[PDB]
Amino acid sequence: SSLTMLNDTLHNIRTTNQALKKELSQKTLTKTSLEEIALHSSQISMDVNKSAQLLARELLHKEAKIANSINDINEQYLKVYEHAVSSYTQMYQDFSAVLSSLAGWISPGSVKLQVNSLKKALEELKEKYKDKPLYPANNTVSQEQANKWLTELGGTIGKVSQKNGGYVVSINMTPIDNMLKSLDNLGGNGEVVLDNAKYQAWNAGFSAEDETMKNNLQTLVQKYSNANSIFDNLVKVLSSTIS
Amino acid sequence: VQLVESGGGLVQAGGSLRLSCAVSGLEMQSHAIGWFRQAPGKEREGVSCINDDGSTTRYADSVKGRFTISRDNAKNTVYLQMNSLKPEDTAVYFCAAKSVWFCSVIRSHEFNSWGQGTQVTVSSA
Image (cartoon, helix red, strand yellow):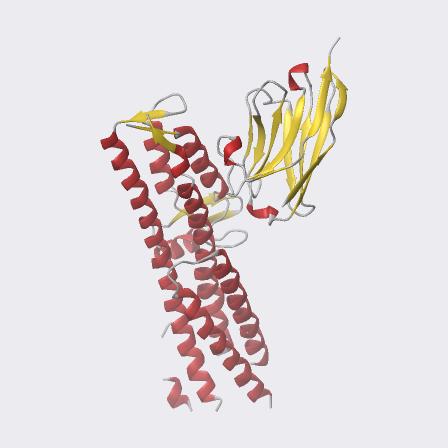
């Protein structure tokens, strides 16, 4: 019967893959959405353990001994995309809160801008996510392992950083650095007055920053869903082989 | 949302006090929490703030190096260690929370919830 227990766990994985796919196809990923994605991918990992624990050649005949390949796609692929999505989504959500506070930092003066309030908020964003890498979730890996995943995640959202014990793929904070440097270039005394024309380029610039970061996140979500779809197709073949 | 301060009282100039803020009614791990003070006649004044995960703390120039803010997301408590107290520090001290995760410049009108406050009185010779 243990062969059928395997098929019941493999079928529980596809059931989770189905819910995971829907969650990732929502335009906006909320803090609630992330909590659900963590549970599903976590439930995935558990059943991938029981599968290997519990563990026609026509149907078998590329990204993927059966246990040493399913545990390979999840450990060194699905879990990586998952945590990358979590970290970047949390960063973006925290960035959106700063932009939401922007309206209350502008007033007529011709526009007066609270450059200090904006700068210090973005500084906190940078400080907060300096030790929240995309990959790995804990500890470190080899510089070569870190680079392998930078190419897979993209140099737009990630950068290999040296940390105690080895290397990680950190969040690329260049966009935040871009904003902070731009704010420094404005000068002032805590506040600054911008002619209407210059403020219009900054407001529209802030909105463009947001859309760029949103697009970065959606691209990463796309890669996680694609990997999950490759993983589901591998599970598919097994559920029909054991049957 | 309820914010309850304790730890105030009377103290001599040069002495110290530790304020404690009991936070009830909000996911404390998601909001910046800070301390304000208001002496009579003078305007409310930002003192310190600590963002939702504690990776940044902020202090007014008047208290930098003397005060220390800390938070315990577990115990739903925020502390303000007040050392090297001066008569200038005499005021009602308020615990306050923001709707956002970050501190930025401490500004009273950007804080969502407020405690009743607790009196700190510093007397010099």
